Image (cartoon, rainbow over all chains, first blue to last red; front, top):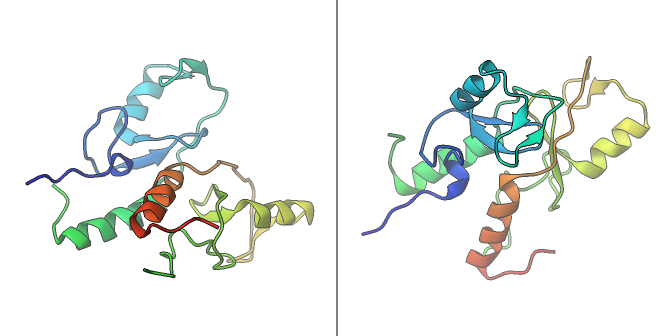
Length: 80
Length: 80
């Protein structure tokens, strides 16, 4: 039928399911890989609104991970 | 209906229902009110581990907001 994961468990930037959740200073959640490229590129601004960024953080997701684990169990499936 | 919400949404510190979570540099989520008291007290150690904190990070809630709204809708219950 139809089975789509909530946007909460998907990377907003790539709109794709991935196992690497990280959070920005603003509290936004994005894929770590994308951010590494973003920082590596030398970009010090938020891609979402093109606003300037004076601080970055490598804080990993916590509750998101726990929630996704429960989500998979409910469906009785494993992450791709 | 379910009168008990998942511990993920519940504040770990007081195990009480609230809507104002923030993150810590250690990837821990605590209620905003509690951390404010901590700062006011001039404490420099993590309450749970009683270990010194060389630094701290303040990040407002994020994906929790979306989940909270959806959760209430699923149960058809108003959020206190």
